[PDB]
């Protein structure tokens, strides 16, 4: 490269990883110094062009030459953006003589982009344990029956005109004739989860647990809350919860863990004392008397049998959050003994909340996705962070969650359906997460992944809940048609991508299952050992990610997108480690020349595939490795 009226795109690069941004999570007064990489001597000038919400205008900040990388192949230019609490967006204008190129969240462009700019959100920090950990989601009733005395028995109670049923372990999740799918209980409880912490934290290595609802409710999924202040008797009691949390936080049964609970705050069950539709409790619920102490907690259109609810589900009356200072905002997150604060405070001290139906939370029965909804989550974040600045907040959302994250005042991240689950599914299994046929090439996969990452600030990207499957969609192994290797590949990608790897109980061994409720089968424990090849791989991959900070908070650079041979390679790197991941999708084995020079891996240095143990030597900026179909190598140094 040289000063020849031409900017060479191949040498350009910038993202907010350690080597290019000294303040990825800036405080309200923090200056942000950035570095732009280019081929050595390729440009004549560079500017950071940023939009400031403070004064509704663009601002140009020149860059100055800073240095060359260890291989002497690139230049590093640096610039500093003035500090202030205002949100800012930036892109780069790179010039060489009369030639100009632009660069933003989606890479290089010949024309100045109008979107996908990078983010600078002052005073927005997500928990670092979330960025660096591995999550394991458990649907309580289906994991492990640690206490048989609390098991819900068949016919114990009837709800919606149907009795409950107890199911034998390993039998179909579908209710037998006469029962309802939502009232089927296998017996899984909190004692069981505690007893299997060694399997989760030691055998596998995950250190973050995310549990579906566990508070008093009549259903087996428990999203129809009856009492937020107590564990459902079938799962145990509050003391059992205190012990489980203590055991999760313990280091005696594996590494220190973290607990994230499911917060169902958009609505309650119709059997909740506040509502009490079936007249089961003393007090006069909102449904029973217009003179109820909790009448304002809900929204009726025609009292008492016509009220706002979750998507028309009668058993799910919608909570009216009213305006700031309301009684509902008090019981949920403003009061000293609010639900959110209660569990974040001792003797519980949980580590976070997953926000159920977070997009609908509103006042007066509104559908959410509006100013009020965003205002409520702003107050919620302020409260939660006040109690514990390291308490996680992850909202449920299926599309682009930018509105609840990019403002830096609401959620730390979201259920990554749009930026992880869907693309991963369509690339590997060739189905959408609902199991309808839908496929994408490797280049489209890389593009999808980058475009969605660009929807979020860097810390949010690193905090996204990335799961292959969950309780509302079909199982990955079912979408894969039982092809376990597809799970192998998915795991390798997952454990090396941006965002929190999240294992939905069972996926580690290849558990199958169709749509709800078949996606909530009882866990087959005879499969929980290295004998299951997927379990053995999972254990190894978690150890690798726990080992390299670069895989959790390092930069991400696309290296190879080959649709002919189905090869996808990308680098994850920071100031210490450089990692080139090489994946092979749906094709026979291939020998790949990995361009590690793009990662500045020096010629003559050695790299080691952390999966196989094979070592290689960098020659002429390359590493030549063989990767079989539906597998991958993790070349690191
Ligand atoms: O009253 C008649 C009827 O009553 C009973 O229930 C019938 C319904 O039961 C089941 O649905 C349950 C579900 O099993 C529960 O888990 C619970 O659902 C909650 C989710 O689990 C949470 O993640 C959260 O989801 C909110 C999201 O909801 C929507 O997403 C849906 C997708 O669109 C869809 O493709 C698929 O993936 O499902 C999801 C979730 O349902 C919404 O679009 C999205 O924006 C939002 O984020 O909250 C949920 C509610 O708390 O409750 C459900 C309702 O009770 C069956 O799955 C359902 O088919 C059935 O209608 C009796 O069981 C039944 O016999 C009787 O006829
Ligand atoms: Ca040039
Ligand atoms: Ca039990
Ligand atoms: Ca009553």
Image (cartoon, rainbow, N blue to C red):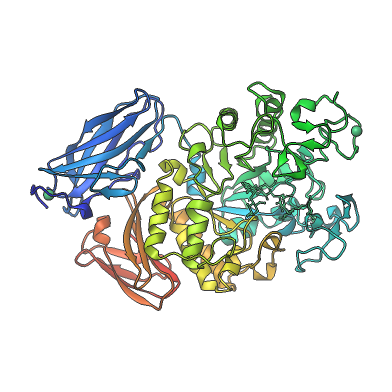
Residue at x 8% of width, y 47% of height: 3
Q: Nearer the viewer, residue 54 or 240?
A: 54
Which residue is the extreme one toward the bottom?
Answer: 588
Residue at x 54% of width, y 32% of height: 389
Q: Nearer the viewer, residue 122 or 634?
A: 122
Location of residue 601 with respect to 590 vertically, above or below: above
Location of residue 95 with respect to 602 vertically, above or below: above
Location of residue 74 with respect to 48 vertically, above or below: below
Location of residue 108 with respect to 428 vertically, above or below: above
Give the image location of residue 322, x and y in percent.
67, 26
- Which of the image's four quarters has the C terminus? bottom left
Give the image location of residue 364, x and y in percent.
69, 29
Q: In this orientation, does residue 581 appear?
A: no
Which residue is the extreme one toward the top?
Answer: 325
- Say which quarter of the image contains residue 586: bottom left
Q: In this orientation, does residue 453 appear?
A: yes
Q: Is residue 443 left or right of residue 431?
A: left
- Say which quarter of the image contains residue 206: bottom right
Which residue is the extreme one toward the front?
Answer: 302
Residue at x 52% of width, y 57% of height: 421
Give the image location of residue 157, x and y in percent.
90, 51
Q: Is residue 271 left or right of residue 598?
A: right
Counting labels gives 0
Give the image location of residue 456, x and y in percent.
43, 43
Q: Is residue 581 left or right of residue 60?
A: right
């Amino acid at each position: 490269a040289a000063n020849d009226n031409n900017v060479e795109w191949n040498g350009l690069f910038h993202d907010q990883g350690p080597l290019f941004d000294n303040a990825p999570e800036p405080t309200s007064t923090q200056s942000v110094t950035l570095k732009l990489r280019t081929f050595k001597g390729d440009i004549t000038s560079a500017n950071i062009k940023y939009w400031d919400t403070a004064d509704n205008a663009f601002h140009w900040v020149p860059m100055v030459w800073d240095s060359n990388d260890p291989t002497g192949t690139f230049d590093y230019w640096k610039g500093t953006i003035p500090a202030s609490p205002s949100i800012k967006y930036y892109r780069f204008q790179i010039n060489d003589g009369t030639s100009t190129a632009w660069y933003n969240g989606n890479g290089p462009s010949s024309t100045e982009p109008n979107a996908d700019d990078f983010y600078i959100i002052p005073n927005f920090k997500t928990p670092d344990w979330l960025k660096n950990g591995v999550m394991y989601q458990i649907f309580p009733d289906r994991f492990y029956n640690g206490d048989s005395s609390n098991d819900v028995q068949t016919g114990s109670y009837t709800y919606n005109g149907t009795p409950t049923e107890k199911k034998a372990w390993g039998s179909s999740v579908y209710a037998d004739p006469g029962y309802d799918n939502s009232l089927v209980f296998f017996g899984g409880d909190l004692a069981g989860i505690d007893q299997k912490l060694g399997y989760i934290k030691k055998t596998l290595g995950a250190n973050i647990l995310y549990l579906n609802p566990i508070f008093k409710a009549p259903t087996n999924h428990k999203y129809d809350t009856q009492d937020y202040m107590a564990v459902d008797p079938a799962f145990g009691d509050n003391s059992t919860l205190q012990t489980l949390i203590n055991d999760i936080h313990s280091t005696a049964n594996g590494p220190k863990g973290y607990l994230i609970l499911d917060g169902v705050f958009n609505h309650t069950g119709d059997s909740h004392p506040w509502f009490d539709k079936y007249n089961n409790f003393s007090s006069q619920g909102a449904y029973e008397s217009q003179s109820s102490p909790w009448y304002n907690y809900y929204t009726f259109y025609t009292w008492p049998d016509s009220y706002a609810s979750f998507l028309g589900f009668n058993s799910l009356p919608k909570l009216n959050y009213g305006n700031s200072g309301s009684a509902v905002r008090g019981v949920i997150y403003n009061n000293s003994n609010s639900v959110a604060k209660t569990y974040l405070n001792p003797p519980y001290s949980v580590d976070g909340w997953r926000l159920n139906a977070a997009q609908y939370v509103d006042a007066n029965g509104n559908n959410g996705s509006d100013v009020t909804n965003h205002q409520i989550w702003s107050e919620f974040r302020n409260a939660v962070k006040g109690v514990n600045s390291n308490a996680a907040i992850i909202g449920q959302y299926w599309g682009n969650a930018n509105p609840w994250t990019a403002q830096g005042n609401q959620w730390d991240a979201a259920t990554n359906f749009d930026g992880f689950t869907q693309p991963v599914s369509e690339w590997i299994t060739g189905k959408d997460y609902q199991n309808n046929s839908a496929s994408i090439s490797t280049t489209q996969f890389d593009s999808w992944l980058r475009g969605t990452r660009a929807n979020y600030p860097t810390n949010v990207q690193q905090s996204m809940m990335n799961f292959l499957s969950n309780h509302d969609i079909t199982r990955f192994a079912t979408r894969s048609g039982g092809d376990l290797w597809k799970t192998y590949l998915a795991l390798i990608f997952q454990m090396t991508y941006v965002g929190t790897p999240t294992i939905y109980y069972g996926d580690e061994y290849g558990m199958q299952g169709g749509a709800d409720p078949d996606n909530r089968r009882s866990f087959d424990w005879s499969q929980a050992t290295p004998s299951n090849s997927a379990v053995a791989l999972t254990q190894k991959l978690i150890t690798i990610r726990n080992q390299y900070p670069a895989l959790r908070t390092g930069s991400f650079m696309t290296l190879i997108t080959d649709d002919t041979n189905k090869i996808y390679s990308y680098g994850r790197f920071d100031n210490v480690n450089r990692i080139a991941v090489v994946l092979n999708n749906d094709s026979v084995s291939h020998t790949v020349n990995v361009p590690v020079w793009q990662l500045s891996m020096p010629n003559g240095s050695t790299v080691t595939d952390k999966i196989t143990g094979h070592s290689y030597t960098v020659q002429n900026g390359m590493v030549t490795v063989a990767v079989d179909g539906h597998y991958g190598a993790v070349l690191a140094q």
